[PDB]
Image (cartoon, rainbow, N blue to C red):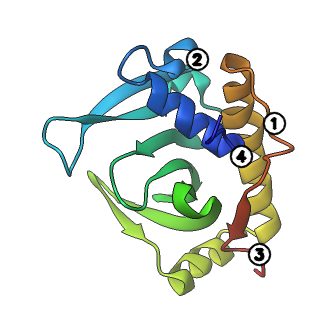
Amino acid sequence: PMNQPKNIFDEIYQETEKTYRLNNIFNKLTDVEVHSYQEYSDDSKFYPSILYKDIAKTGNYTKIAIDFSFLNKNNNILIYFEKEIGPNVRVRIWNKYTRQDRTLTKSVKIALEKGDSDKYIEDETQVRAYLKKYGITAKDLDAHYEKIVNQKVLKDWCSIYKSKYSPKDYGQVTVKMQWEKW
């Protein structure tokens, strides 16, 4: 009552924190696997991480995941996904909702595949050079975000939880997009 969700990301965060030790709400979503990974700050605890199953991934999308950080000072949900954009190169679109300032920050990174390993690139100038090389515009980034975050991840949430929000009306949330002027 005192701390009801103010937007769809609060709703996901709070219902997952309420259920992840008892019977994770995402057990209800058949397209994903639920994982438990060791918390860095408390050796006695695990955080939940959601990974879309291969059956549930489309076209060039290689990964779709939701990580929950409940224990740290900048606690948050992170929804991210990755798509191949050229030979040995993937774009990663990174959408982090920070609880303490009710802010969703959308950003773009690059992964370079060098055989076994990935090398990760986040510096804005380098990222934009890769995007320009492979012809990815800000409008393309919006379309990828709409397709995966709104039409898949958040639509999936609304299929397992009776949301007070929706993929087209997030609620009260400050949205900051790295590529807004690109």
Residue marked by disc 2: 29
- The residue furthest bottom is 125
Residue 6: numbered disc: 4
The reply to whether the C-beta atoms of the residues labelled 4 and 1 are less than 8 Å apart is no
3 vs 1, front mark: 1
Q: Looking at the picture, which amino acid does disc 3 mark? A: Glu
**Secondary element type, mark 3:** loop
Q: Please tell me which residue lies in front, 182 or 97.
A: 97
Q: Is residue 24 above or below residue 152?
A: above
Identified at 43% across, 54% down, the residue is 75
Under circle 1, the secondary element is loop
- Of the two numbered discs 3 and 2 on the same chain, state the one appearing first in sequence: 2
Seen as rendered, the residue at the extreme right is 168
Of labels 2 and 4, earlier in sequence is 4
The residue at which mark 1 appears reads as: 166
Placement of 112 over or under 61, stated as above or below: below
The residues bearing labels 3 and 2 have C-alpha atoms spaced at a distance of 32 Å
Residue at which label 3 appears: 180
